[PDB]
Image (cartoon, rainbow, N blue to C red):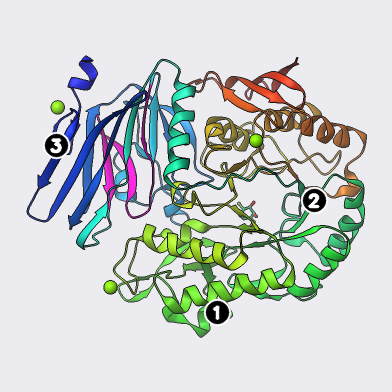
Amino acid sequence: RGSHMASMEIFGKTFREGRFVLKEKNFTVEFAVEKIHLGWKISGRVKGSPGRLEVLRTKAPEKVLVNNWQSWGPCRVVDAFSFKPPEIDPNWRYTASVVPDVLERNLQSDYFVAEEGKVYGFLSSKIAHPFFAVEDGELVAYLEYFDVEFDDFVPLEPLVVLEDPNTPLLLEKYAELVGMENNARVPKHTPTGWCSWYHYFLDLTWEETLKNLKLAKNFPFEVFQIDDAYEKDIGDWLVTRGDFPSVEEMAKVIAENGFIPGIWTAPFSVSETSDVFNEHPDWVVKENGEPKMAYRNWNKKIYALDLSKDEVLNWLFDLFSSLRKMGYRYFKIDFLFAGAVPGERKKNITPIQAFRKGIETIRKAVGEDSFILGCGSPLLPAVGCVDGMRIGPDTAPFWGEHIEDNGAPAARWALRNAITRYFMHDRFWLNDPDCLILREEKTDLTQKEKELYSYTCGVLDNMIIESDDLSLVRDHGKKVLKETLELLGGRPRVQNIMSEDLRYEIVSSGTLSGNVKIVVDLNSREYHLEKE
Ligand SMILES: *[C@@H]1C=C(CO)[C@H](O)[C@H](O)[C@H]1F
Ligand SMILES: [Mg+2]
Ligand SMILES: [Mg+2]
Ligand SMILES: [Mg+2]
């Protein structure tokens, strides 16, 4: 009976409970509008050529929590009316949007959008990409089918519209419904461990690795994970460089030392220089019959594997099978968005359908006993496949006090996303807030910043992985980690999720330290923690 709800349109008609049919020239939608706890659900099926299918239209709120489709992109509150299109980096187009025609004109939010007291959220992204655009003062929900044709009906991605003054509660409920819809993997045990990247970056040597592997026996690390550095090229995962042994030999040394071997790949990415690409130029997504650049990194054009091709999926299966055989049981799989870039594939399936085949192949290959950590990944499409997911831009050994909020590395913005995507944790997957950087030297992080970052992550019950030259972690670093792990185990809530001043009140019930509250200020870099 609300005046806002009378103002809503669903598939172009007025919002009310029922079963409905939209027949147009090019497509047919059959949908149901059902009442559910705390709002409404729209579900059904579509066939024909739905293209960019308008699902919902309502008046655009002034302040919206918007969400980028992938790990690194911002989840933040913006003013819907004063939006100006960003300059899009030609090297990273698709991190910004899978539909960049939208974002060069209009405010875009992927999967969900919130305002004070309301959540609009799609429960899945299996076939279509679900997004919202603010178009001349209206919020419009779309399902993008990328010009794919369906002879027979396929399921819509369901949409929920939830309403209640407790917006955090709504986001948590939304995420519960996503997790149900996609059979989310929420492991009962969270791995601790070590990651090479945020100290050594691409300059990691096996020599330095071995030093840290020895020191790691003194730290509470289960996993020891080799990051980007070991591989000869992007796509040539089983060929090492420099002073590294074979990929199999690395696993055996790590295992011999009593750790779970972890390894980094970018499994949907092949560089223009790689052996795999040069051997198989028809394995990639194309544009005008020619390889289409998915992004530019490592000073190379990087192409996307065409995950509609059986030869490609077999290759992935064989790769990850091989790695599992060697003893790897922790897989950090990066730049996953590449697999979902728009373009020409062998089969006329959506980039999301392709993406899902790819990640499902990896899951099958590594088995149920392996931990998969997603990163640089579309979020909804991965639910049910990954165990953990990076939900923020990279951290860094500096705060980023005047670094722009554009998805680039900075502790300040990594932590912001850990806070604003908190509700995904223990519902979609385990949230990975990125590594703690606790070293005393070779850092521009202050002790107070280290504390703020680490204690926040602990209160949020998020994955705790450390990334340091362990030689440089002394009493202060060890204490911060110890105290962090004491804050795990709870059910967190960010009580003021629509905050625009980067000050957040965060509670967590039932931690190893009881009920806890941390108030954090990411501008002033202050926290105040109460443990009861
Ligand atoms: C993806 C990329 C790298 C290094 O190339 C790191 O592993 C980062 O944490 C990931 F998001
Ligand atoms: Mg109207
Ligand atoms: Mg076909
Ligand atoms: Mg938990």
Assign the N terminus to one quadrant of the image.
top left
Residue position marked by numbered label 3 in the rendering: 12
Spatial CA distance of label 3 from label 2 is 53 Å
Bounds of the magenta segment? 118-144
Q: Nearer the viewer, residue 459 or 276?
A: 459
Q: Is mark 1 within 8 Å of ligand 1?
A: no
Residue position marked by numbered label 2 in the rendering: 222
Ligand 2 is found in which quarter of the picture?
top left
Q: Give the residue displayed 73% in from the left and 28% down from the top.
A: 455
Disc assigned to residue 276: 1
Mark 3 vs mark 2: give the one in front. Answer: 2
Spatial CA distance of label 1 from label 2 is 33 Å
Furthest residue in direction left, as rendered: 25
Please provide percent x and percent y for residue 14: 14, 29
Query: Tag 2 or tag 1, which sits nearer the N-term?
Result: 2
Marks 3 & 2, CB-CB < 8 Å contact: no
